[PDB]
Image (spheres, rainbow over the protein chains, first blue to last red):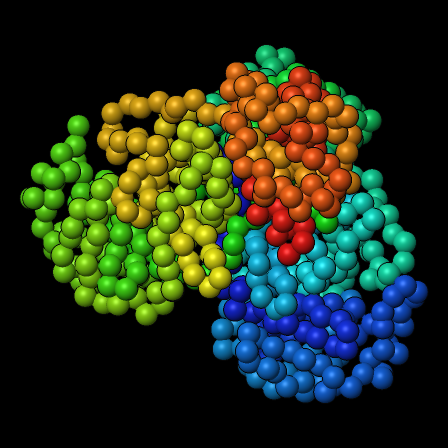
Length: 298
Length: 294
């Protein structure tokens, strides 16, 4: 029993973290094979006006880099721009490089953050990509370059490298192709997070988890059609539900169909009335159907 | 900025997980040096564990690290654990200690199945000596740990789930948290209360992150609050010196936060704090200080 936002074990990723320093900048990089990827902000000088990164790279001195894995220092062979990242060729292969892929995540999907400082992992936690392409992380100074990942079949899927914090304190990364999530700029200038909506399919996953865990007080006897719900959703800060295939297993396990949960969501969106569901006092969209199924049934 | 319940990185513990099978039972063990620790439940069919051990055949154990099987040399009872001596040293054994956690303290759970880590998450020991974990069948023997300056402190091995679905483990000395029994007989969890010193730490994190809507202008003395706490599902406040730096940084004293807690209890759920339930008690003062300041 239980539902917790959990991370996949971080060991295989820990071995890939490096410290990347240039001048007065210090952040984290990801060392895979003979390449280190890090945010290009490390070569910026520095704030608070628009950075010409191409110029910064053109005047770079390779020897001014300090890149290390614990005590092992890496020689820099070459540097190339990769969107919002530097792709740094180093003189050594990371012998502990896991089997890996890159994949850009989409809003509503979950992944793991390995928060790193000074080139060493400090903490690991799960997140879910919001509809405005930000995550609610926890990062302080030095965290840039912390990776996000999923693990499938022992293959590590890297999907995020930490880039910046917005004025409201939420967090934006790029994918490993160097494409910033949400199109935010890796510039010191003013940027505000876009509007966000609760991912209804994730909220549904959470309520199914609640039912599996014996929380049923909030459950409606009423129903509402997906069509009717979707009309209400867009005036009420939640996403539309298009397909319900992802709920077949959970509906079968519980005997509760999506339509009853949608009615429940409507009454729980305003108010939990002083009660809790699995410890929550407000609807959460941080869990996906896949997470819930894996967590309840393996 | 931000506040998240995190786990310390699990890599150093992952290489210590083994699968331990006996008869029809399979669970997880912790392999350190030439010893494997696991819940004694694995040799059970009320249970007389001394009897079960007296008839046990060593060759009936199957202990594996990945596809490598370890030879069993001997077995000794250790409270609710077995200490199993094996014929090989774990060459990836970290520097480690054992320490029993106390209510209100945080640690990390590495949830394991079939002798392999599957998930990692932070927990906090509740006032009734249970944790709010997530574990399904096969999780027994999953370890709890903290990492303190290069040393792994092992503090928990998973033992059982109660009717309410909260979780009980033993320490690595084999002493069951809360005194619950490793028996199939039905047991119910003791009453639990929110850990107030942790709620205080959380509210300080909130202030540091610019959340102030809930902040009372009133004050209540610690001991008078404590009298109220014990009738309102909250623990007493005993330690206050730990809040000194947080009070200094925010300009808010504990007495003001205690009055805020009373008010939050009165419109419970009316608004989130940093996206959490307002009376969140899973973060300790140390956790908060580390996430705010490093």
